[PDB]
Image 1 (cartoon, rainbow over the protein chains, first blue to last red):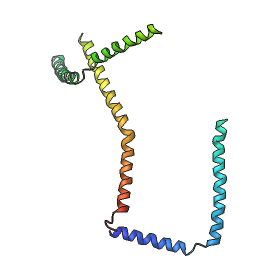
Image 2 (cartoon, chains in turn yellow, brown, orange; image 1 turned 45 degrees about the horizontal axis):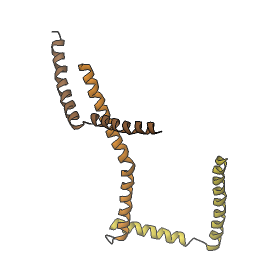
Image 3 (cartoon, each protein chain N blue to C red; image 1 turned 45 degrees about the vertical axis):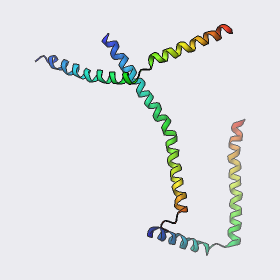
Image 4 (cartoon, helix red, strand yellow; image 1 turned 60 degrees about the vertical axis):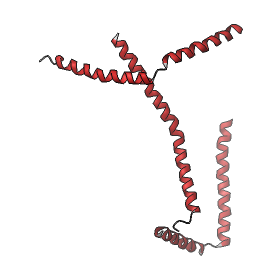
Length: 54
Length: 53
Length: 53
Protein backbone atom coordinates (compact mmCIF):
# COMPACT_ATOMS: atom_id res chain seq x y z
CA UNK A 1 0.00 0.00 0.00
CA UNK A 2 3.03 2.25 -0.50
CA UNK A 3 2.27 3.35 -4.04
CA UNK A 4 -1.28 4.33 -3.11
CA UNK A 5 -0.15 6.44 -0.15
CA UNK A 6 2.53 8.18 -2.23
CA UNK A 7 0.03 8.98 -4.97
CA UNK A 8 -2.47 10.34 -2.45
CA UNK A 9 0.24 12.51 -0.87
CA UNK A 10 1.20 13.94 -4.26
CA UNK A 11 -2.41 14.69 -5.18
CA UNK A 12 -3.20 16.24 -1.79
CA UNK A 13 -0.14 18.50 -1.98
CA UNK A 14 -0.98 19.58 -5.53
CA UNK A 15 -4.57 20.28 -4.47
CA UNK A 16 -3.40 22.39 -1.53
CA UNK A 17 -0.94 24.28 -3.74
CA UNK A 18 -3.61 25.11 -6.32
CA UNK A 19 -6.12 25.96 -3.57
CA UNK A 20 -3.85 28.54 -1.91
CA UNK A 21 -3.83 30.36 -5.27
CA UNK A 22 -7.62 30.36 -5.83
CA UNK A 23 -8.88 33.91 -5.37
CA UNK A 24 -12.61 33.75 -4.54
CA UNK A 25 -14.03 36.84 -6.28
CA UNK A 26 -11.89 36.78 -9.43
CA UNK A 27 -12.27 33.07 -10.12
CA UNK A 28 -15.98 33.32 -9.29
CA UNK A 29 -16.39 35.98 -11.97
CA UNK A 30 -14.34 33.91 -14.42
CA UNK A 31 -16.45 30.82 -13.69
CA UNK A 32 -19.62 32.81 -14.37
CA UNK A 33 -18.18 34.05 -17.68
CA UNK A 34 -17.18 30.50 -18.63
CA UNK A 35 -20.71 29.32 -17.82
CA UNK A 36 -22.08 32.04 -20.10
CA UNK A 37 -19.81 31.05 -22.99
CA UNK A 38 -20.65 27.36 -22.51
CA UNK A 39 -24.32 28.32 -22.66
CA UNK A 40 -23.76 30.06 -26.00
CA UNK A 41 -21.94 27.00 -27.34
CA UNK A 42 -24.68 24.66 -26.17
CA UNK A 43 -27.35 26.84 -27.77
CA UNK A 44 -25.56 26.66 -31.12
CA UNK A 45 -25.24 22.89 -30.67
CA UNK A 46 -29.01 22.61 -30.20
CA UNK A 47 -29.71 24.84 -33.20
CA UNK A 48 -27.65 22.40 -35.26
CA UNK A 49 -30.37 19.72 -34.92
CA UNK A 50 -33.21 22.24 -34.81
CA UNK A 51 -32.18 22.81 -38.43
CA UNK A 52 -32.10 19.11 -39.36
CA UNK A 53 -35.71 18.84 -38.20
CA UNK A 54 -36.84 21.31 -40.86
CA UNK B 1 6.64 -42.32 -62.66
CA UNK B 2 3.08 -41.36 -63.56
CA UNK B 3 2.76 -39.07 -60.54
CA UNK B 4 -0.98 -39.71 -60.82
CA UNK B 5 -0.43 -43.22 -59.43
CA UNK B 6 0.53 -41.60 -56.11
CA UNK B 7 -1.34 -38.30 -56.14
CA UNK B 8 -4.68 -39.96 -56.78
CA UNK B 9 -4.16 -42.15 -53.70
CA UNK B 10 -3.15 -39.10 -51.66
CA UNK B 11 -6.38 -37.31 -52.59
CA UNK B 12 -8.39 -40.51 -52.09
CA UNK B 13 -7.08 -40.79 -48.52
CA UNK B 14 -7.77 -37.11 -47.84
CA UNK B 15 -11.31 -37.87 -49.00
CA UNK B 16 -11.37 -40.32 -46.08
CA UNK B 17 -10.93 -37.56 -43.51
CA UNK B 18 -13.43 -35.51 -45.52
CA UNK B 19 -16.04 -38.27 -45.26
CA UNK B 20 -15.33 -38.76 -41.55
CA UNK B 21 -15.91 -35.05 -40.89
CA UNK B 22 -19.07 -35.18 -43.03
CA UNK B 23 -20.42 -38.16 -41.09
CA UNK B 24 -19.70 -36.52 -37.73
CA UNK B 25 -21.31 -33.23 -38.75
CA UNK B 26 -24.40 -34.91 -40.19
CA UNK B 27 -24.87 -37.21 -37.20
CA UNK B 28 -24.70 -34.09 -35.02
CA UNK B 29 -26.71 -31.89 -37.40
CA UNK B 30 -29.89 -33.55 -38.63
CA UNK B 31 -32.18 -30.52 -39.08
CA UNK B 32 -33.28 -30.59 -42.72
CA UNK B 33 -36.26 -32.98 -42.65
CA UNK B 34 -37.46 -31.27 -39.46
CA UNK B 35 -37.25 -27.85 -41.12
CA UNK B 36 -39.24 -29.06 -44.13
CA UNK B 37 -41.80 -30.58 -41.76
CA UNK B 38 -42.19 -27.18 -40.09
CA UNK B 39 -42.55 -25.64 -43.55
CA UNK B 40 -45.37 -28.03 -44.45
CA UNK B 41 -47.04 -27.50 -41.10
CA UNK B 42 -47.03 -23.71 -41.43
CA UNK B 43 -48.07 -23.82 -45.10
CA UNK B 44 -51.15 -25.82 -44.15
CA UNK B 45 -52.50 -23.19 -41.76
CA UNK B 46 -51.42 -20.42 -44.14
CA UNK B 47 -53.46 -22.00 -46.94
CA UNK B 48 -56.40 -22.32 -44.55
CA UNK B 49 -56.12 -18.60 -43.79
CA UNK B 50 -55.79 -17.78 -47.50
CA UNK B 51 -59.00 -19.67 -48.27
CA UNK B 52 -60.76 -17.99 -45.33
CA UNK B 53 -59.75 -14.56 -46.64
CA UNK C 1 -23.51 -38.36 -58.08
CA UNK C 2 -20.40 -38.06 -55.90
CA UNK C 3 -19.98 -34.49 -57.14
CA UNK C 4 -23.49 -33.72 -55.87
CA UNK C 5 -22.63 -35.41 -52.56
CA UNK C 6 -19.56 -33.24 -52.03
CA UNK C 7 -21.63 -30.16 -52.87
CA UNK C 8 -24.20 -31.09 -50.21
CA UNK C 9 -21.46 -31.63 -47.62
CA UNK C 10 -19.92 -28.23 -48.34
CA UNK C 11 -23.33 -26.54 -48.14
CA UNK C 12 -23.94 -28.01 -44.69
CA UNK C 13 -20.48 -26.97 -43.48
CA UNK C 14 -21.20 -23.44 -44.74
CA UNK C 15 -24.44 -23.41 -42.74
CA UNK C 16 -22.57 -24.51 -39.61
CA UNK C 17 -19.96 -21.82 -40.08
CA UNK C 18 -22.65 -19.16 -40.45
CA UNK C 19 -24.38 -20.44 -37.31
CA UNK C 20 -21.16 -20.04 -35.32
CA UNK C 21 -20.81 -16.58 -36.86
CA UNK C 22 -24.26 -15.66 -35.51
CA UNK C 23 -23.26 -17.06 -32.11
CA UNK C 24 -20.22 -14.78 -31.96
CA UNK C 25 -22.31 -11.82 -33.13
CA UNK C 26 -24.73 -12.38 -30.29
CA UNK C 27 -21.99 -12.83 -27.67
CA UNK C 28 -19.91 -9.79 -28.58
CA UNK C 29 -22.47 -7.06 -27.91
CA UNK C 30 -23.05 -8.03 -24.27
CA UNK C 31 -19.77 -9.59 -23.12
CA UNK C 32 -18.02 -6.21 -23.33
CA UNK C 33 -20.75 -4.50 -21.31
CA UNK C 34 -20.47 -7.22 -18.67
CA UNK C 35 -16.69 -6.78 -18.63
CA UNK C 36 -17.15 -3.08 -17.92
CA UNK C 37 -19.78 -3.74 -15.25
CA UNK C 38 -17.25 -6.03 -13.57
CA UNK C 39 -14.64 -3.25 -13.57
CA UNK C 40 -17.18 -0.84 -12.07
CA UNK C 41 -18.00 -3.39 -9.35
CA UNK C 42 -14.27 -3.78 -8.67
CA UNK C 43 -13.92 -0.01 -8.27
CA UNK C 44 -16.88 0.04 -5.88
CA UNK C 45 -15.39 -2.78 -3.80
CA UNK C 46 -11.99 -1.07 -3.71
CA UNK C 47 -13.61 2.15 -2.49
CA UNK C 48 -15.62 0.18 0.09
CA UNK C 49 -13.00 -2.22 1.42
CA UNK C 50 -10.32 -1.11 3.84
CA UNK C 51 -7.74 -3.36 2.23
CA UNK C 52 -4.47 -1.50 1.96
CA UNK C 53 -4.86 2.25 2.16
